[PDB]
Image (tube, rainbow, N blue to C red; front, side, top):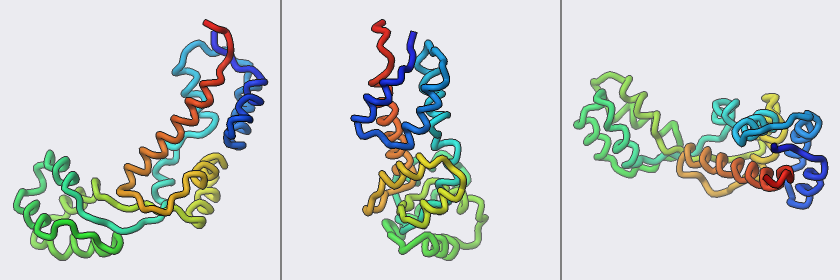
Length: 195
């Protein structure tokens, strides 16, 4: 049977774990609950410490928005939908690899270059756009004002990056990898039943 013991926190303290992580883990120490499965422990740890998927949309909205560039993979994996004609695909590929200044320029080009056709396909094209991600102090301040757990903002600041991300999905994947690494480091110091 897996458990949790008080000295596990002291052992983790030598691993440079986030202080907010320890503050959220203190509930786990005081819960006096004996788990038996990996899933029922990991899911509860994510819930108590804080889940990015709970406020993923809010985090996405609060994030700064940067430049937009066209990607061949976007059309390649959006060709499943039959709404967009292949002549529209050729028209968009005519201005291939157009790295616009920001989202406004891309929106203006999409509304201007494409004409005499319905705009629902234009809106659906925006589903898989490569948009850069920027992290600033004001966005983190807004996130903190959004009543999210402080560990979210702490680890977001710990993931500060000046280089612009290729797309938001890559930033989310990096965040998922970071939280998975933290979870694995935590589980490395689990109870010592020995079985």
